[PDB]
Image (cartoon, rainbow over all chains, first blue to last red; front, side, top):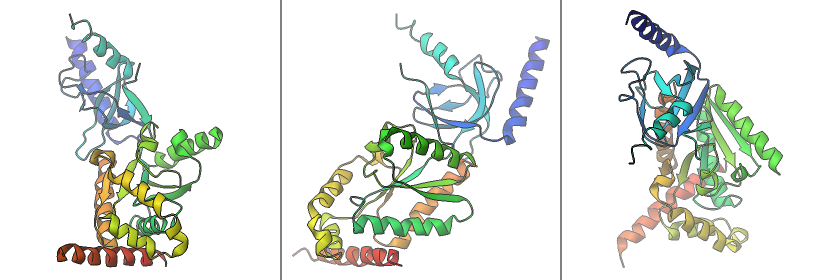
Length: 273
Length: 25
């Protein structure tokens, strides 16, 4: 009806007016959704579509059932997004047809960049190889990046300092600037897997164990003593599945590893802007 | 034997060492 053509028209005018509004917050989805099928969508054909573990930038709220935002991927058009409420409905109306974990996790508007490997942090080889990358980033993305240290154990996400650091990370990402964390306690992807930080794990992967072993020897007797715990840490990371990391710096030349990481962060920047 | 592994080791070592020395700056 007539009053329906105005609502849809206006709904669509709210959708476009929001096209350039600030990113209120972000969510990582825990379920898939096919909005192109959702008939109740305020505007036929404006429903977002996403698989589980995707990221969404919420611009504004339309109603209790719908938000307005977009998928965090290049060419991510603004759209209507079902709220946890509406998703719950849908989850139940598909339950009755067969004869609690939330649909969304609120995450930082920019996923925290975190480095792991080639081995244990605290030792010269890993610390220096990662230091070289932090310096490169401080330079390549100067003007739109924040690189900060976190000594608090984030994998716990003292429990007060941890909370305070979680909040600090959210604040840093609010401006949509790149956020890189030099987190001393994170040596393995699984240590952040159950947090709500949804980091961009960058694996600095040394080709072979023989090589890493010789890099350690290059450091001197002091480092060589802790040879066994560095090699084990290396084995654990290497025994991890690919999907466990977002970026795998595979190259043996620093500048190539840097360009790899930069290309990736540049695609991310376009995706979030 | 397997002179390619030896070559590979020399290539990776040299690169990774330079990577480390660059951070020593």
